Image 1 (cartoon, helix red, strand yellow):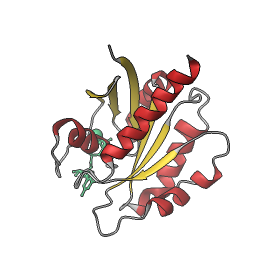
Image 2 (cartoon, protein in one colour):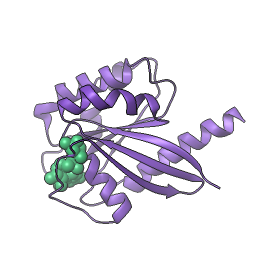
Image 3 (cartoon, helix red, strand yellow):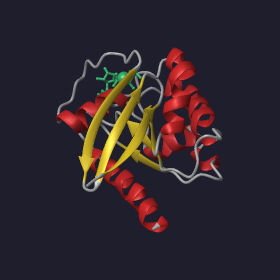
Image 4 (cartoon, protein in one colour):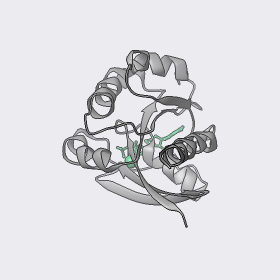
Amino acid sequence: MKTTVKVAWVGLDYAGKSTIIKRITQGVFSDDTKRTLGLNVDEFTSDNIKFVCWDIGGLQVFRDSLWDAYIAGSSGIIYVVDSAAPERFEEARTELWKWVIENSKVGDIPILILANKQDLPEARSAGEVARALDLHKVLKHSYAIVPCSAASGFNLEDALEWLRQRITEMILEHH
Ligand SMILES: Nc1nc2c(ncn2[C@@H]2O[C@H](COP(=O)(O)OP(=O)(O)OP(=O)(O)O)[C@@H](O)[C@H]2O)c(=O)[nH]1
Ligand SMILES: [Mg+2]
């Protein structure tokens, strides 16, 4: 029997949340993924864990209507950033801090930041994305940052393994 955990996939519109989930669940890269106009629900299993992926649209309208509930009901949060869109790093930092770092509804749950689109020539490194999001100023929450690509699959297995390990560690430490 597997334990069900709900994971909220958040991040700005165009960050690559839906494309990463498609690469993991279908094994294929879609370079023409369409904007999510609400919620996509998908599943993937990794060992004793059934991951229920809540892929929420990142457009402003969906942050204000849907993000609060799915973030508050999740067991883990994945915040995806387009590393090749530095014109939106300040906006991505603002939303990460409002909806995750300083959101009182987020307890001591796993927080994984994915610095996505590493395959693109203008992609900033994981270190550069961490500094742009002020991750080095996060004082009370644990977090991980992983550079990845839905196009090549780079680090997607390792990122999912990190989440499975953190969720399993919480279960084992409590027992
Ligand atoms: N080259 C490249 N393109 C990517 C990658 N991830 C996503 N894309 C592309 O980036 C665009 C936006 O990806 P989406 O998956 O729709 O982004 P999203 O975060 O789900 O956006 P919303 O649905 O608006 O929340 C699409 O054209 C994707 O094909 C990646 O790692 N590399
Ligand atoms: Mg989407």
